[PDB]
Image (cartoon, rainbow, N blue to C red):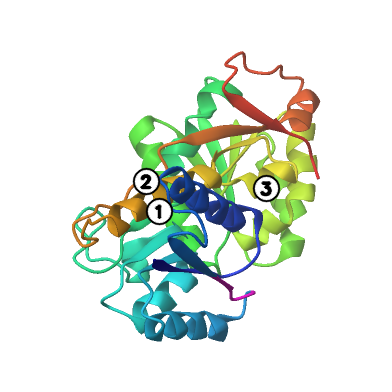
Amino acid sequence: VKKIGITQLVEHPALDATRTGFVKALEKNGFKDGENIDIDFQNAQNDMPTTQSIASKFASDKKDLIFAISTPSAQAAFNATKDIPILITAVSDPVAAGLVKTLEKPGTNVSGTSDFVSVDKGLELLKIFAPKAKTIGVMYNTSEVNSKVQVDALKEYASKNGFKVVEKGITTSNEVNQGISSLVGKIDVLYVPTDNLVASSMPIVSKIATENKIPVIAAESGPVEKGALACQGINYEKLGYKTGEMAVKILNGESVSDMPVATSDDTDIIVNEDILKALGMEKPSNENISYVKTK
């Protein structure tokens, strides 16, 4: 019989879906719950101390495998053991989190899947939603450290592909309406990074961008649902299933320090149906595109 611990940070559609898929991969490969495996599911419920508890508990439980969902959940797992295999998922940056020596060759007890989506993947959509675009807009928070990383990525994409960039650096939420408005007439497309300031004030940005025919490309599905045009979001159930297939490999034998970190692979284009009609644009004819409505 097998003891598998699942440590999740919080209940959340993306994270919940990686769980669902991970289980299914085990089931189709013959590891039914309470038959020859037992799954210890622990939600930390967004309590950051309780991620540590779950880790330590699973260490002294001597679990066969620790499936960890989210960067904090995975970090806590790494503290509590350096001799139980720990499969991650929903972690953007494994090397910056300190879970793995290099992405290709683990050199530790920690393999799994990343949920990273590059600025490159996102801007493949310029072809579809902003054809012959010359100049990309980007509004972002100077305070948020991971935004300027994402903006530097965009300037480096822009430079290398022949686009110009227009930046609005802002700090406070009240500056937004003014910001997005100052970008009217100067940009062919706006890119919304994963950035708490701007991701949270979408209903405003949606309004002012859509009124001037400006397409809004987002780095994830959340801002699409709330009035951005499209994103290159991941199917988290599939990223889970992938990670669940990597489990079956460890159970039936494989050594996890050799196992390389598999990636998103299957990412689907998610388009806001409604925002599309409001831009006067018609649906792309490639049928492998998903659609959603605003809130």
- Where residue 114 appears, as percent x and y from the top left, is 40, 53
Name above or below for residue 209 compared with residue 58: above
In percent of the image, x 38 and y 74: which residue is there? 63
| Left-right relation of 115 to 293 | left
In percent of the image, x 32 and y 69: which residue is there? 99
User: Badge 1: how crowded within 10 Å, few (<14), some, or many (20+)?
Assistant: many
The part of the image, by quadrant, that contains residue 231 is top right
**97 falls in the magenta region:** no
Disc 3 marks a residue whose amino acid type is Pro
In the structure shown, which secondary structural element does the residue marked by tag 3 occupy? Answer: helix
Q: Quadrant of the N terminus?
A: bottom left
Are the two marked residues, 1 and 2, in contact with CB atoms closer than 8 angstroms? yes
Q: Which residues are magenta?
A: 41-45
Which of pointers 1 and 2 lies earlier in the amino acid sequence? 1
Q: Which residue is mark 1?
A: 114
Name above or below for residue 284 compared with residue 256: above
| Left-right relation of 111 to 66 | left
Disc 1 marks a residue whose amino acid type is Ser
Are the two marked residues, 3 and 2, in contact with CB atoms closer than 8 angstroms? no
- Where residue 70 appears, as percent x and y from the top left, is 50, 64
